[PDB]
Length: 162
Ligand SMILES: *[C@@H](O)[C@@H]1CCC(=O)NCCCCC[C@@H](CCCCC)OC(=O)N[C@@H](CC(C)C)C(=O)N1
Image 1 (cartoon, rainbow, N blue to C red):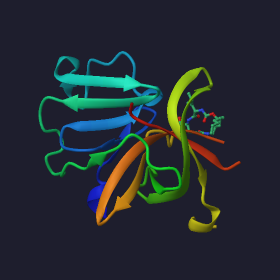
Image 2 (image 1 turned 60 degrees about the vertical axis):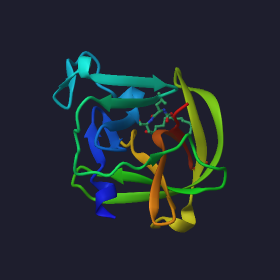
Image 3 (image 1 turned 135 degrees about the horizontal axis):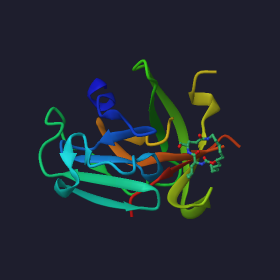
């Protein structure tokens, strides 16, 4: 639904995602360095928790009070089909279907990633992206379980919270 896509926000060299009015997640390596604020808020008002290329910001005030809070999980069960909510600069919404594999630690191009590997689903997709969220549906509810970190055997990795 559109409220889910309204959570996907351009951030640094990629994207991030509003889990709730106060919680923003992204991939560490797209985060700007040497800034005094994020989204106009001083660093002194933001609780930053990051590890394994997963970054979480918790703001002191409601930044996106238009949003309900949704569930953030540490990866998903092996075999889950996730959608990676990729946005283009136009605002075009391009969900990418991925079959999720195992959670592991990996060194990718110098950075330790705590992530879950997956494979792009050729059969479920039409015949600057780091930070995009990996989501899947539980009932009519959406769950977020990672952020796009790496891709190359049509393989992807999302960083996950630990
Ligand atoms: C967002 O910043 C990118 C998204 C992936 C991407 O752009 N892939 C195209 C370049 C491929 C470079 C090789 C891959 C190998 C990953 C293998 C595991 C599937 O490297 C990355 O994807 N590196 C990654 C940055 C590191 C620091 C995690 C990256 O480009 N992420």
